[PDB]
Each structure stands twice: as C-alpha cells, then as structure tokens.
Image (cartoon, coloured by chain):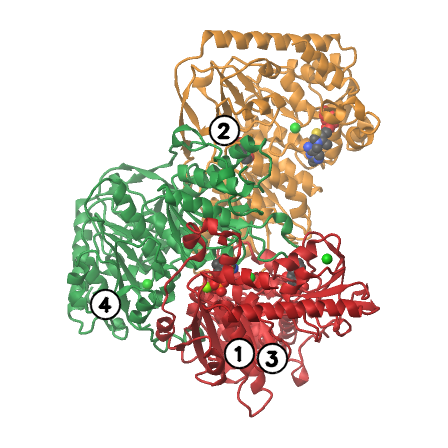
Chain colours: A green, B red, C orange
Amino acid sequence: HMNPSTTQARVVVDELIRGGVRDVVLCPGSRNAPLAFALQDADRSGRIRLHVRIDERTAGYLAIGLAIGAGAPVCVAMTSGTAVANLGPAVVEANYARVPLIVLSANRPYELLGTGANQTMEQLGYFGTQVRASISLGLAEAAPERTSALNATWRSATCRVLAAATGARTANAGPVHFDIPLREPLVPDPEPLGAVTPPGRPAGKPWTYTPPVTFDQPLDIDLSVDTVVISGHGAGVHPNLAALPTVAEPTAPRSGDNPLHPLALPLLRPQQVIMLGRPTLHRPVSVLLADAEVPVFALTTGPRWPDVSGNSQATGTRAVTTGAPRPAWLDRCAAMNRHAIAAVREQLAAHPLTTGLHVAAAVSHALRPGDQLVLGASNPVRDVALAGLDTRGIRVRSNRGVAGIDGTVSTAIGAALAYEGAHERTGSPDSPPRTIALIGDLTFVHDSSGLLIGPTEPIPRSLTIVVSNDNGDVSSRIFGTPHDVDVGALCRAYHVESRQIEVDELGPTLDQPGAGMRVLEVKADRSSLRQLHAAIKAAL
Amino acid sequence: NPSTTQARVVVDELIRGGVRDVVLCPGSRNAPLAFALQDADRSGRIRLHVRIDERTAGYLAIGLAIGAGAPVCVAMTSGTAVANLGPAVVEANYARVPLIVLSANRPYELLGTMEQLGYFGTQVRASISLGLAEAAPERTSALNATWRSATCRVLAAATGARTANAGPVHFDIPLREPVTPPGRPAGKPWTYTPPVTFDQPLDIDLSVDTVVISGHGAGVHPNLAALPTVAEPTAPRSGDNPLHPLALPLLRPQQVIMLGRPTLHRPVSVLLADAEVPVFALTTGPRWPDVSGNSQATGTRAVTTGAPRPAWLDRCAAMNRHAIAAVREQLAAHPLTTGLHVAAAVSHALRPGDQLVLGASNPVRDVALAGLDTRGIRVRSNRGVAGIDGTVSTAIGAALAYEGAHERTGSPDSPPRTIALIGDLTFVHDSSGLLIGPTEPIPRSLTIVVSNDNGGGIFELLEQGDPRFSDVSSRIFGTPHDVDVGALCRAYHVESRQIEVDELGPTLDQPGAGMRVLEVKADRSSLRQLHAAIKAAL
Amino acid sequence: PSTTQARVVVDELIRGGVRDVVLCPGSRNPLAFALQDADRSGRIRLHVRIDERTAGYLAIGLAIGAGAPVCVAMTSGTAVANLGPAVVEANYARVPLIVLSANRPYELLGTTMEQLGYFGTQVRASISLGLAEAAPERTSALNATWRSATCRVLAAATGARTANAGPVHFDIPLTPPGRPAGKPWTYTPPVTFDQPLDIDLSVDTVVISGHGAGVHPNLAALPTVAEPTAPRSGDNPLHPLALPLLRPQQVIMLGRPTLHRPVSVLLADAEVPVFALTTGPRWPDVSGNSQATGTRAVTTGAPRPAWLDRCAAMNRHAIAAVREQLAAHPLTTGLHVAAAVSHALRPGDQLVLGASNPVRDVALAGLDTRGIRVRSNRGVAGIDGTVSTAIGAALAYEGAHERTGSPDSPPRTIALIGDLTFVHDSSGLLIGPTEPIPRSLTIVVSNDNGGGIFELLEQGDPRFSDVSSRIFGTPHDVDVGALCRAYHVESRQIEVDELGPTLDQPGAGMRVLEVKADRSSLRQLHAAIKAAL
Ligand SMILES: Cc1ncc(C[n+]2csc(CCOP(=O)(O)OP(=O)(O)O)c2C)c(N)n1
Ligand SMILES: Cc1ncc(C[n+]2csc(CCOP(=O)(O)OP(=O)(O)O)c2C)c(N)n1
Ligand SMILES: O=C(O)c1cc(O)c2ccccc2c1O
Ligand SMILES: O=C(O)c1cc(O)c2ccccc2c1O
Ligand SMILES: [Cl-]
Ligand SMILES: [Cl-]
Ligand SMILES: [Cl-]
Ligand SMILES: [Cl-]
Ligand SMILES: [Mg+2]
Ligand SMILES: [Mg+2]
C-alpha cells in the first residue's frame, strides 16, 4: 500500500502538530519531498501554516521569529547537504536565547555516507553541543506487519524531539536536530491504491504526554539592604520584587513600576544586587557585576545561570524575601532616575542633527499598548534603553543570544506572523495588532533577502520596519566608506512598499492603518553621536 | 609585543607557501594576524578581500582557490564565524579545495570568539594550534623555527602535499589580550615538501566494449584518449571521442572506467550500479566512489592492453550523432526559451581560455546536454555537495584569482573572461555576494548569466514533476519568487541587462564593466515536455 | 602562581562536598601536591591506584557509597582512554564524577592529552579554568573566578540545578580565602523537580521499579515488581516470575527497568498504558509504549480487592515454586548462592551486586531490600570494574558511619559477583599498604567457571551444545584462591551451607569467599521452576 517514506513523513508531521507546532518553515529540495508532501497537505486542511523560503539561513531566523512571537515550537524542514549547514547561525542563536527550534533535516540513508553519493555529508552531529538533542529516526522498513510497531517508535521519537526543544522536562528550551534518512520512492503512490496514516492517540493527545514541569530553587534575600534589581533576557516575573529599583533590558518583562535608568546605576552605590535572567547589554551594569564587594543573587527560570558575575553569592529560581527596602534608598534611586531621564531628554533637544537616538525615541513614543516591538540587537536595543521606553503592555523581541547581525529582518517577519496568528484564535474580530521593527541600515541590507516572500506564502498583516540609516583593525576598512545601498531599491526588488520619511513624520506615519508589510527609512547621522553621548554623560 | 612578531612570521611563511589571497570579515575580537596582513597588503605581497557576510566570505575564498589552484586563507573574527563558514568548509572538504581557516583563541579566559559546532572534527584535514608567544631574546632562532614549521604543516595538510587529498585546515593562533626574524634564503619555504606522486596501476583490457565516465576531480589519462567518454563539465578532457550523456542508454557497455567522482545523469548511476558491468575506479586521491557497491577495482592510472573494437567505436559514434541531432532539432522546434536554450547559447559563445563557472540544478546539467567542448576551457562548479548557496561569490573569487594569474604572466592582452551560468534561485540565494566595497578587489571580466525561469526548474524533470502532482507542486517545489533581478543588481551598483537568448551571443562578445549580470527570462512550464520530446526523438 | 590556583580549587571542592579523591601516578601532575596537603591535614582521603581503569571504577564506588561527588585526577596520555568505561557508567547511572585534567597552552598542539569522542557525548559539562597570571593586583578577582567555576563543576556533577547528576570534565591548565564558615562560594539550594501525573488506581495496576527509582507513599498498596537496586516504598511485593501469570491493565514504571524479559514484554504491550515516573529529566520507553511521564502520582480511586487477591496468590505460588525447586536440585548453582547471601543479610548492611546472573538471581530469590542498601552498575550493565566499585562503595559507606561517632564496628558490605566478573577486575584487589583499605568488605564469588547467563538464553538451547562452549561459556580454569593470595587478600573456598555462618564472622577487612557452582544444570533448573508455576 502506502510506501514507507510517505507513511513515515505523514506520521511525523501528525505527531508534530499534536505537540503544538502551528508553523513550519519549508525549504525546497528533492530528498525532503516526503516531508514536503505531508506538510503541504497539513497546510491544505488548516492544521498548520506553511512558510516556504529559498535561503535556508534566513529561513532559520524566520523560524526563530515564528517561535518567539507566540511561544510555540517551530519546525524548519530542509533537504540534505549544505542546506543543513546553513541552519548553523540560527541554531547558535536559538541555543543562547533558548528558542524551541526543530531542525527537521532529510537525509540519504546512512549506508551511503562515505561512498561519494551526491549531496551527502555528515549531517547527524553537525551541530555538536549547540543543540539540546541530535535524534535520528531510523530508515523506514517496507514491512506492513511491523507498521503497528513503527508507528509507536516514530511518534515516541517525535515526542522526545518536542520535549527537548520546548524544555518540557528540563526547563532548558533550545534547538533540536531531527534527522530523517529517506530512500526512494520519495513521492506518494497513486491515491486510488492508497492507505490511511497509522493513527495516534484518541482526541489529538500527544503520543507521550508531558504535564507541566516545575523547577523550584528558593533563595533567602533580605530586602532592607539597599538593593537594585538588574533584569536581562529570559528573566522571569517576580511579584515580591516589584517595589525595588530595577534596571531592565528592553526584552526583559517588568515585574513592577519602579524603573531605574541604566545611566543612573554608576552614580549610585547599591550594597546588594539581584540579577534576573542573563544581563548583557549595559557596560555600567557589567562594571557593577565585576566589583567583588557588592553581593549578587542570581535568579533564573532555567538551570543555566549566568557567569557575567564573579561574586555570585547564590543562584536560584525565586526569592523568599525578608524585610522591606529603606524609603530613603527608594527616594534616592527615583530621584536619580528622574535626573537621568531629563539629561537624556535635554541633550536630545539641544542636538541639531537627527541621530539614531532621535529615531529610537520617536519609535518609543509612537508605541501603544498591545504592540510588538522587534529590535536589532546592535544599536537599536541600546538606543531604546537610553530613551527609557516603558515596556509595560508591549512585547519586545530581540535576538539577544549572540546579538548577531544575521537574520534580523526574517525574525521580525516571523514574530509578526506569529503574533497576528495568536490574535485570530482568541476570537476577537478586531484588527490584528501592530508589529514595529527598528533596525539599522547595515543590518537591513545584510538580511534584505529576508524580505523575499513568495506570492503564495503568508505575509504579515501589520508589520512596519523602521530602518535608521546612518550609512554605516584593517577588517574595518569597509566601514570607512558608506556601503551606499539604496534601501528603496532593495524594497522594490523584493516587491515591498517603502517610504523615505523624516523623524518628525515617524509618529503620524506609524499610525497610518495596516498596509500589509512596509519599510520606513529615516535618514540619521553618525558623525555627531560621540558629542551627543558625551553631552548626555556630562549632563548627568 | 611578541604576538605581533608571531603574526609577522606566520604571514611571511604563508606567503612563502603560495598564499596569494586572504579573506577577512570584521568581528568583535581582533582578527588573527590582522595588522600583519594589512602590512602585507600594502607591500603587495598579498591581496586582501573584506566582506560583511561571513557565509559569502567563505565561498569567495573557495572561488579564489579553485580559480588558480592556490591555497587561500580566511580569518574568522566573530562568534558567528564558525556557523557561517560551515557550508564553505563542507564544500572544501568534498571538493578537495585548499582552504586555511585562521582563528585566535584566548587562553587566559574561562571556557565552559568561537561558537563550537560539531563539523570541524569531521571536515578538516588537520587542526593545528600554534601556542602562546612569550618574549625570549635567547630563543628567537628557536621560536622562528617552531612557528614556521607548524605553518608548513598547515599548508602541506591543506594542499595535500603528502596525502594527495587537499582540503580545509583549522589553524589556531592563541593571543594574549593587549623587526621580523628571518626565514630560509631565496624565499623558499621553511620545510621543503616535494609534492608526492600517489600511484596505483590497474590492468584494464580495452578490447572489451568500454566507456569512460569522468566526473569531478578526474585525472587526465592519455592512454584512454580513444575510448568513448561521457565527461562532466568540470572534468578535464583527455581525448577527442566524446559520448553524449543521452546516448548512454542506447548502448550496452561491457566495461566502465570511472574517473573521479561522477555526480550527474541518472543513466550514469544506473550503469554504474549494474552488477553485470565491471566498474574500475581511477582517482587522483585516496578517496574512491561506488554507486551500489559495484566498484570492482580502484587505482590511479590504467595499464592498458588491447584497443577498442572499430565496431564499438562506430556504434558509439552513431548513437552520439542521434543524441546531438535530437537536442538541436527539438530545441529549434520549441517555441519558448528554457534554461536549456540559454545553456546552448552560452556554450556556443565561449572562446579558448575563458573560465566557466556553472551553478548547480539544471545549468550544469544543461551545459552537458548542449555538447560543450571543454578543451581549452577552464570549468568550475561546486560539485562537492552541489549546493546552490555561495555560487555568486564563488564566481567572483574564481574570476579574481584567474585574472591575477594573467597579470603575473605580464601579457599586455586584456584579462581573460570568466562567464558564470546560474539559475535564479541560485542567484537569489547569494545575491549579497555582489555587495563589494569600492576599496576591495573587484573582477575586471566577470559576466554572470542568470537563466531566470522564476523558480526551481529541475523539479519539473523529477518524480514530483508528474502531472498528478500539478496542484500541489507549485508551492513546495517550483517556489516562484517574483524577484526583480535588475533592481537587485541596481541596488548593489552592478551593471545589469535583460536580454533575449538570441542576443546572448553578441552581448558576451562585447566587453563592459569589470562585473555585470545578464538576465535571460525563461519558462519551466514546458521543461518536462521538451525533455520528453528529446527522449522520443533519440 | 599555579600552586595557588591548585590550592584554591581544592579548598572549594572540599567546601563542595568532596571527601575522597582518586589519582594515578603519571608523567606529570601541582594539583597532586595540593591534594596531598589536604590529605595529611585530614580534609580529604586520597586513593592511589596504578590501573587507571580500576581507578575510575573505584571513584564510582566512592560516589554511590554515601552519595557525594568524587574527583579523579588524570596524569598521563592514556588516562582518557582508560577512564572511558567509568565515565560511560557514570553518565547512564547518573553518578557525580569529576575528572580533573591539565592542558599545556604553551605547546604546539595538533602536530598527556589524548582526545577521543566520548567526552562530548557523556559528560554533563566541560569547564576549562584558564591560564593564571602574575599581577597580585587582581588575586582577589582570580580567587572568585576559580571558586565560582569550581562551584559550576560541582553543580553540574551533582545535578544541583538540573536534577541529572553525571560526569564532568574539569581542565586546570598549567591562599586567597573562601566565604566565611566554610560555605561554598556560590550557594545553590538543591532543586525540586515536579511533574504531577493523574493516575486512576482503580484500574488493575502493577508497579515496576528499576534503577534510579524514587519512593512513592501513595503507591505503597499496589503490587510491586522491584529491581534489587530500587528503593521499596510499600510491602506488597510481586515476585517477577508471577508477572506472566497475571494480566495487568495499567503499569506504573519507576526509574529505568533493565531486568526480566516478562517485564520487557509487558511494558511493550500496546494494550497496556504505561506511566513513567522518574526522578530526573530523562524517561525510558520500551517500544514507544510510554503514554505519559512524570515525577509523582496524583491518585484517584483504589485498587480492586479482586485484583490484589489475584496478585498475592501468584506471588505466593512463585516464591514457593522457587523455594521448592531449589531444594530438589542436587547440585549447587549460582541461584543457590544468591538465596544464601540474601538470607544472611541484616538491616543496615550494604549489598553490591555484579551484573549477569547475580543481580537477576537475587531477584529470583526474593530478597527483602528493606533496611539494606543495594548497589549495582546498571547504567550499562558491564562486568568490568565491579570489584573496585565494591571497594569504593565499602570505603565511603564506612566513612559515613565513622563520622556519626557510632561506637559499633563499621556496617557490613557484602558483594555477590560471578567468576568472569572477578577476573575482569582482579587488579582492583591490588591496593598498596599506605592506601585506604575496607574494614568490613566480603566479596562472595559464585564460581561456575564461565558465563552462566548464556545457558538461559537462546544460545543455551541444546541444539547449539557442540558449538557454544568456546564462544559463550568461556571456561577459564583460574585458581581464585591463588589470585587472592598473590594480591595479599584473605581467601577461602566454602560450600553454600557454610556461607551464612562465615558471613556472620568478622575477619580481615577484605576477604574473598569463593563458592563452587554449576551451570550445566542451569537451563534445566529454570525450566523446572517455570513448570512449577
Ligand atoms: C543550499 C541548497 N539548498 C537547497 C538545495 C536543493 N535544490 C537543488 S536544485 C534546487 C533549485 C535551484 O533552482 P535554480 O537555481 O533556479 O535552477 P533551475 O534548475 O531552475 O535552473 C534546489 C532548491 C540545494 N541544492 N542546495
Ligand atoms: C565489559 C563487558 N563485556 C561483556 C559483557 C557481556 N556479558 C554480559 S553477562 C556476561 C557473562 C559474565 O559471567 P559471570 O560474571 O561469570 O556471571 P554469571 O552469569 O556466570 O553468574 C558477559 C560477558 C558485559 N556485560 N560487560
Ligand atoms: O575522486 C574524488 O575527487 C572524490 C572526492 C570526494 O570528496 C569523495 C568522497 C567520498 C567518496 C569518494 C570521493 C572521491 O572519489
Ligand atoms: O530514570 C533514570 O534513572 C534514567 C537513567 C538513564 O540513564 C536513562 C537513559 C535513557 C533514557 C531514560 C533514562 C532514565 O529514565
Ligand atoms: Cl540593527
Ligand atoms: Cl542491447
Ligand atoms: Cl546538482
Ligand atoms: Cl545484566
Ligand atoms: Mg530557476
Ligand atoms: Mg559465572
């Protein structure tokens, strides 16, 4: 009846859907045709949304966007060869950002490794320690009597792939390499003489159910000691710490309503630091975490705990708090937070030229509750932190794992599609929410291929990309001249609407109703930034 | 600083070892041998190429190595460099390309930049770490010897000087966070390793009806020059008796001599798997291919007795004329331009001495179906893993190294031409390879011909191209993109022109800017029927 | 500079719970001197061996004896290869093993550190300290960097944050105080790993508990087939031979089962839901039949009286069939020796079981694990290193009893192993005069002169009788008594009826009791028990 490659591909796709996979990114190939056929039919029946891309490296960052936008595991299926190697960059990012990314690689049978067979390499284990698991399905046997047993083993392995990627039993979500060797026949047989897919558990249940896991590690912390909370990427929400002064990275969730501008920390003298997540962005933050006199308590949601400090007195998951912060200490930190905010506000106005900070400040004001903000992990994240954005009621995403230039555009597109997707299922007939991306010009040009979306492929409903164009070791001689790439020409090539506006119009133009996907380019300056940052520092 | 001394010794020995080009990317950490390479660039001892995209940088290095046969260095500088260099390193492994990867590790920092993947173990020929530099005026003669000896190991491993198996090498130079000692006289390398002769004679009787199938990495065998030879475009031709690939299924060879690693044509793979046909594998290195475990014997050269029967050579020649006529006649009888028409136009426009860079998918297959005469012509293609990524940067590096070899011959004639034939998906995959800063070296005679059928044409010719999949194959296989290629080249400031297949000939004869892209629109909705008409007219 | 780094690291390892360290004489290795100072000062115990393989398995025993992390110090360019087996066992049995290495960063590399592939697949973490400097202006900062990293090593080995103990590779490439009151530099409270599973005990349920299983009070009433190394939670045991006689409709699987074919068949039956309750993040599956994973059970309902009565009946029939067929058998088999050891055990004893038949035979003899501590290398079920495992297990066990100030002599550690197992790791008996030696260790060897377990497998079928003596039985004809005397260890040959009384007498700290056994009748015995059911 049904050939083994088709049966295996349909069973795997079926178990992945039951595991919560709503979006799959597919790259074209011949060896992965079984997976391609099963995925396309699951897209026809509405069980998943399929995204086709041509460039596997940007496809991996699209899949990362599809996962951080709503929280679901996301699969990316590709053929054998360098197609798997091109997933390298996205796997590394997903490792340090803890993104549940499933690399579903088709492969030749392993017996062909070493024979010179076309388009065949050492795929299994290619990703080394960067993945949470390298799992290989077997080669499918042509034995309809073993069909019952193979369905159980295939579905149980797919569940193991899903459990490791989502961190269902480790609290350490990350990328997983799921390698599937496939042999001919690679296409489905004539459907008149066809079969039905071996069934899973009744009522759409996963083959192996993993109920919610709890990882608890309580820590004693006395709050009467003058305490500042520094929250970075992957930080959890802690209600018992919402009163304390908090220096929060843009991608960190806010526990309370007592902010502290990063520029204010070096001008204060905390006696005790509570570190939430993986702080990385601010240098004065990094300075304070080096100082050995100030005790540091680390609180993480997963088992990995950051090494950005040397005087880590203790690491846990939550705090059992004793006491309450001194009101004089609270008055001091709030006083200095207002002083830092005003210093940034005055020097921005006192500056003649539009810099990247002005663009970042303009986007911050235009934000509204419910919006999603995607930030290039270079300057845009630091700039929005200097402009003191209030991340309450907005979801802020950024590839803070390795903070690479790769794939920023694709991540924005993916996060938008995932966000607007979860808005449909909540039943609201209201319009889809907004996703605004702020990225530099060198990052936009570098991942301009990420703008490519085939005519038949899903397109974000309300994504606006704001490109702050500052036109910019012997390896730094390429930065000595402007790359001179017309942002509008790239957008025309990839059939994307573009507009070159000014920072004054940034607000009103961002409020124009949803026009699908669009790119807004703001011209900015880089020559005067050294004076602006020196002006702000002197104003403090 | 004893480290800047180390860096100057290594760069000198690498130049003595034949390295004429190095590729750099800006990174968070300082580049390995960053400043020493810069002095070597201004001195004219070496040519530096800088790129932003580390993936396109790896493939540019491959192009710089295969265009002239020299070893090439790429200097990793960031924490994403290992991941992005993966594709090029894998291709360098399977295509046997001398690729040196320079990295600088920090021994005073806690471990537990570089992001370690698992491929370095399986792909590289050697992993050599220099060692930390320490000041010692009484050991300058000794540290000069250790550094240059290890540098000679790195080059010998990468070029296959002692193994006959070129490939990528990982060279690590540890650094401590912040004149040149001499080498051998006359510019000679520190440790002279004479290239080795790797010899495996094999007895083959040529009176048995024999066909030769030469693939990637095949050698030149003068004693086999008379036999009917089905040769891939990248294989150097050794005779004047070509056998069209479509004529192979109309014959019954009793013996097959397989040169190098064949990767094209399903009739070839069916023949090589036939257990009733002895297959003899002749390779230039230690690796050897088998299709279905049907390689009877391995070697490097044939010790031949006998000669092909004149009746056998006549049958092969008759079947060859039928195949050539069928392709020419059916192409003329087809209204729409396909990628196969473009391949025949590019093939008829080449001249002796030109370089041809062929992308994967149909272009490299279509050129073979067009009967391209590869003699006097240098043909390149990344057949190691047959990826469609990095083919634009590979052509650019191939043009740059090929032109530099013509400059060093001192001929006043214009630089030789490099013509690249790639699909549209291939072009879209690595369009970023066109972004070259005005400071960097740019080719002077590179023409990229893009055969644009708005998607993946080869899938029309495979099993998923069957009409019973017509309703499902468009999205997941054809994958149209609707990209404006001229607008892309415009954005990157590359001369671009859309032309018809009839104007393709004369357009390549006229020179132009040192780099330009010629886009020919094509159709893939008639591809499967054009190929069926060719098979039936055989 | 390196002497200070080595002495800082040793202090944090002692503050982290390390009480024993194994090392081997090697071509080099500072850490040796620092470890030496702590040994004379009494802060750790040092154990030296010549055989690096046996050194790795000694450290495993030192870990599972009391539950502490243990360090082993490689010193040559053969230690990685020789420590391989012990690292693999530590990985699969979740044993806190710290492997200490020393790289040379000022030397040409790649043209005492032999790299194999197992480190990247077996260890929980790989942490290299980094080269030391000389500026005493940052000695306070270097102190924190070393003690923090050492705390990372200990946390990965003991599973402090991941609940998955295992081996760790620590590279120290070639006195600033710690936190006051001897606490570790970075405190990490042990983590609680929780997954509640809804299970209806009203369905006819059996509990199968294997290696690494936890203790479950709300499952104490259910019939329980428990492997020897499993800790028992209730008092309704179900003899393993009774399982094929019953027809359960639901299975709760604790830990990682590895024994008894009937169990493997039951766990694979697609008509029976299996629930895997584990103590860590890994979970086992036989044929993809595990339908849910968890760490504890939220139980509704109660077991039917009809189901419990049926289970108690077949249990009784099985214990009686084994106790009776063992009496009718004239020759002494390894199954008689397992029953003799089990009935000679008192509460508070430690029992070390080798693989092959000894671990299975003790289960067939129905030993009551309550009050006693069973140890076995069930991670990969190998016959190597079992002797050194029992020596280290004895040492750490008596060490925990010495530190409680009890006046009574050390508690008993009895090891039941086979002959092939004894020969495989006979070198582990070679212990120098200055090295620590157990004071209450008895190694009972059931010597049937070959592999008895093979007579019970398909190769033991009589149609292979003429072709299976060489390649499965493997007779050795080794004089165990002469071997023990050569290594200066007490040895005595006794009969099964003499095993109990001799075990009750305390003798030299290490004694090897060898009982002659037969395997030619093993397949016939087991066929007799099956027919008696
Ligand atoms: C990196 C990579 N990803 C995917 C593939 C699978 N693949 C093989 S041929 C092909 C289509 C290429 O299309 P195009 O370059 O337009 O060529 P055409 O066959 O249409 O001439 C694809 C995606 C590959 N070979 N390499
Ligand atoms: C290192 C290792 N090699 C081989 C095996 C395979 N094996 C399993 S049981 C066994 C026989 C051991 O015989 P013995 O220790 O005398 O025990 P018996 O079954 O006779 O009681 C062997 C070789 C193993 N488990 N470990
Ligand atoms: O001859 C060659 O060039 C060549 C190159 C390769 O990368 C091979 C890989 C596997 C098996 C055979 C191979 C081979 O024969
Ligand atoms: O529970 C345990 O102790 C345990 C231990 C292991 O080493 C495992 C290995 C693979 C699969 C499951 C495992 C498991 O459940
Ligand atoms: Cl950016
Ligand atoms: Cl014929
Ligand atoms: Cl190809
Ligand atoms: Cl066993
Ligand atoms: Mg195409
Ligand atoms: Mg035995």
Image height check: is C112 above or below C122? below
- Quadrant showing the C terminus of chain C: top right
The span from disc 2 to disc 3 (Cα, nearest Å) is 68 Å
Asked if residue B460 can be seen in this view, the reply is yes
Q: Do the residues bearing badges 2 and 3 touch, measured as CB atoms within 8 Å?
A: no
**Residues behind callouts 2 and 3 on a single chain:** no
Q: CA distance from mark 1 to mark 2?
A: 61 Å
**Real-space Cα distance between discs 4 and 2?**
56 Å
* Near-viewer residue (C481 or B213): B213
**Residue under label 2:** C290
Q: Which residue is mark 4?
A: A499
- The residue that appears at 24% across and 38% down in the rendered structure is A323
Work out whether C36 lies above or below B236. Answer: above
Q: Residue at x 67, y 11 (%)?
A: C322
Label 2: few (<14), some or many (≥20) within 10 Å?
A: many
According to the image, label 1 marks what residue?
A: B418
Mark 1 or mark 2, which is nearer to you? 1
Q: Secondary structure at mark 1?
A: strand
Q: Look at label 2 and name its amino acid.
A: Ser
Closer to the camera in the image, B453 or B321 = B321
Residue where numbered disc 3 is placed: B181
The disc, 3 or 1, on the residue closer to the chain's N-terminal end is: 3
- The answer to whether the residues at label 1 and label 2 have Cβ atoms under 8 Å apart is no
Mark 4 CB within 8 Å of ligand 5: no
Secondary structure beneath disc 3? loop
**Which of the two discs, 3 and 4, sits closer to the camera?**
4
What amino acid type should be assigned to the residue bearing mark 3?
Pro
Q: Is residue C69 left or right of residue C509?
A: left
Q: Residues within 10 Å of mark 1 (few under 14, many from 20)?
A: many
User: Residue C528: where, in percent of width, then height?
Assistant: 72, 12
Numbered disc total: 4
Q: Are marks 3 and 1 in contact (CB under 8 Å)?
A: no
